[PDB]
Image (cartoon, coloured by chain):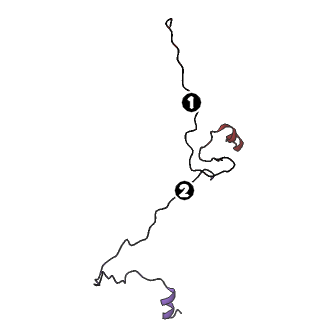
Chain colours: A red, B purple
Amino acid sequence: STSTSQIAVEYPIPVYRFIVSVGDEKIPFNSVSGLDISYDTIEYRDGVG
Amino acid sequence: STSTSQIAVEYPIPVYRFIVSVGDEKIPFNSVSGLDISYDTIEYRDGVG
């Protein structure tokens, strides 16, 4: 017996309903991809271990 | 008391009496099947709903 306000707090969000807004315009899009953070890694390693 | 000219206007048509004509020839056939229209459906769906 989950209440309908409990689902708004506990449940994951489905992807298919989204708003894309390009600048001042907002335009309906079929899909959005990419959009991820990434970092190169720097590795130092010396002789003592 | 339906008149016989009212049946020609209001009543449905029975299937069993038909004429098939292939090109210039007309030839008697036992049954005809298929012969229907059909269309694929194209569905677009974007993010605003």
Q: Report the residue that reaches farthest toward the right.
A: A5
Q: Residue at x 49, y 85 (%)?
A: B11
Question: x, y percentage for residue A18?
Answer: 63, 47
Q: Is residue B37 above or below residue A10?
A: below
Q: Is residue A10 above or below residue B41?
A: above
> Would you identify the image quadrant in which residue A14 lies?
top right
Q: Residue at x 36, y 73 (%)?
A: B33
> Disc 2 versus disc 1: distance between alpha carbons?
33 Å
How many numbered circles does the render carry? 2
Camera-nearest residue between B45 and B9: B45
Question: x, y percentage for residue B45?
Answer: 56, 54
Q: Nearer the viewer, mark 2 or mark 1?
A: 1
Camera-nearest residue between A10 and A31: A31
Question: x, y percentage for residue A13?
Answer: 63, 41
- Kindly identify which numbered label has been placed on residue B44: 2
- Residue A47 vs residue B47: left or right? left
Q: Report the residue that reaches farthest toward the front.
A: A23
